[PDB]
Image 1: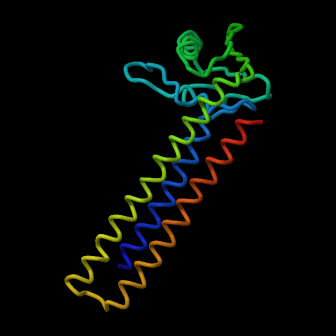
Image 2 (image 1 turned 30 degrees about the vertical axis):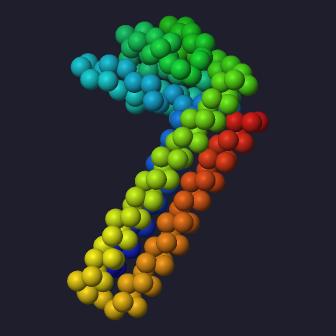
Image 3 (image 1 turned 180 degrees about the vertical axis):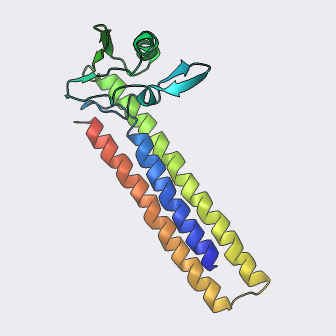
Length: 183
């Protein structure tokens, strides 16, 4: 029960980080290095995030300017971003992929709002499920009677509270990502 309640919490804050990392891959205008990072490119055999083969994707703002550490690589990166959903105009002057991220249409915007609610909804039922494995061990702990019925129930009520706390972190983040999107 110490083990359970301590493992559950720790794994819930690991999920609040994963959701935070994901919602930041949601392109929104303002532009940023996270968007350009679900995009992979076949590197000598396998496939690789562009943000792992590129030059620190420099912001500037309106635009975003790249630069690999590989001349013969610029080709598949720009085509990578052509395949991309992001919807961006990329050039490559001869050793730099420069991209103009346009403004969002009210249509694509409110489509992102939908992938963002979706992403949080997945983040949430993961913390609910994490709570379920803790609760279903506390419960066992009282069944085989390895703690006072007054000790387990106290840990039950803490779990309920931590889970719940973490569930609203996930609602906050989304709400934030949502308003970011409705500039």
